[PDB]
């Protein structure tokens, strides 16, 4: 159910596969920031979630370097899948750049993404 | 210099291998009962100008014994030198129902040291 | 633009007055559910269609309840017909040190005038 | 306890007064970023915290406008005061800049400061 192709509000594309032991792998395509083309993502998810109507906790990372570009940045997404009519992944993310120690205070962006398969 | 074992101040320990393909893999020890698979990515080609190396990993807090129905992501950067550290901000997201989704997510920071 | 009554999607409601010198003052909503708010905004935003930087704080104490916590919202006002306040918030509950790593929740809210 | 002069790890100066009512008032001066001289802050704190040795939840905002400069941004600190031989305010902060709709994805920095007497 998590496996498949997803989109967010910004129009990025995130092609995950959810493996057996809570492994998340795929590519990420973002509509924004220092980034063109596909980046490798990997993460993890809760492979044994709750029956009680609770969602499925997951997260992934993307290092924004590929064969064409290196932003010297990395983003992590934290959130939960929710199945149903409109299945969706509500996330919060943290994007950190490689900064000198004098710029580390301003090294990290925070934001939230919502993914859907539409 | 990311490869190796790292300690935070909370008593948590992580062992990670920094692969040549920007891969970050290892275990997180929050007692095998407490070890969790870690997976992430890092800037395999950092600047040499005094910048740290951006990185992120994730841990889903399920293993063969427990499941907290949650996941933590770390996003931060490796800083070399004789006093090396990984400085991070994390997001802990819990499995909740929709009416509880506002209370799904803890934020924090950790520093990691080679010790 | 900001001054007035804002509603989020959780039904919850706040009324604020932005004073000329970036003050934000109002209440966050049932008497028992009303709390004092205070914040600050950029009283002189760019004129480039950037929104208006602002934030505020609610400590969750009133004469009826005390949750021993504070929420702060950091976001920006985006005016016009359909105005929105898009925020991010940190909720921190007083904790012992031992539990301080789990002291602070994060999320986001979007408040509208309707 | 909370009332006083505070500094963070950045060499920033946080000068705050806590009201009986739960109001925070004061001035912040940051060592870093698009800032010089003092800025107005306002906040709230729990004016009747727990008895369990829990910290005092609190928060404040600085919109970064003063007569010297304007960064079109606001930082919200959220945290707790911790009494003791080493009084300390541990916080997480959100710095949101006014951005266009297009750049809103990168409007908000997150970070953490701890303030010492
Ligand atoms: O460093 C860069 O400029 C590249 C960052 C990638 C864009 C971010 S990651 C969080 C958010 N979600 C997206 O789909 N895009 C942005
Ligand atoms: O937008 C700007 O450049 C002004 C922001 C002020 C710098 C920040 S606020 C969070 C952090 N704590 C400090 O003492 N300084 C920085």
Image (cartoon, coloured by chain):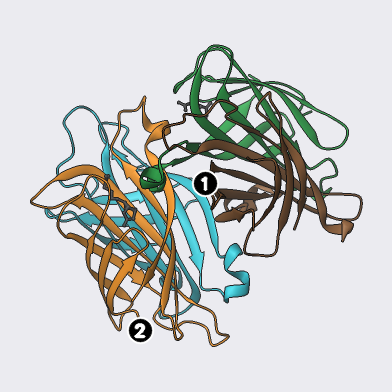
Chain colours: A green, B brown, C cyan, D orange
Q: What's the chain of the residue with tag 2?
A: D
| Mark 2, residue position | D1
> Residue D53 appears in which quarter of the rendering?
bottom right
How many other residues sit within 10 Å of disc 1, few (<14), some (14-19) or many (≥20)? few
> Where residue B66 appears, x then y in whole percent?
86, 55
> Residue B37 appears in which quarter of the rendering?
top right
**Residue at figure coordinates x 75%, y 58% from the top left:** B30
> Where residue D107 appears, x then y in whole percent?
37, 37
Mark yes or no: residue C81 visible.
yes
Q: Mark 1 touching mark 2, by CB under 8 A?
A: no
Query: From what the image shows, is residue A29 above or below residue C47?
Result: above
Distance, label 1 to label 2, CA atoms, is: 38 Å
| Mark 1, residue position | B81
**Residue at figure coordinates x 27%, y 31% from the top left:** C81
Question: Which is nearer the eye, B23 or C80?
Answer: B23
Question: Which is nearer the eye, B60 or B100?
Answer: B60
From the image, state whether disc 1 or disc 2 is nearer to you. Answer: 1
**Residue at figure coordinates x 28%, y 37% from the top left:** D98
* Residue farthest along the right direction in this orientation: B64
């Amino acid at each position: 159910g998590i496996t498949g192709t997803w989109y967010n509000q910004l129009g990025s594309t995130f092609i995950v596969t959810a493996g057996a032991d809570g492994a998340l792998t795929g590519t990420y395509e973002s509509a924004v920031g220092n980034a063109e083309s596909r980046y490798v993502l990997t993460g993890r998810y809760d492979s044994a979630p709750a029956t009680d109507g609770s969602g499925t906790a997951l997260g992934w990372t993307v290092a924004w370097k590929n064969n064409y570009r290196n932003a010297h940045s990395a983003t992590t997404w934290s959130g939960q899948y929710v199945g149903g009519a409109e299945a969706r992944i509500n996330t919060q993310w943290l994007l950190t750049s490689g900064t000198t120690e004098a710029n580390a205070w301003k090294s990290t962006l925070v934001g939230h993404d919502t993914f859907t398969k539409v």
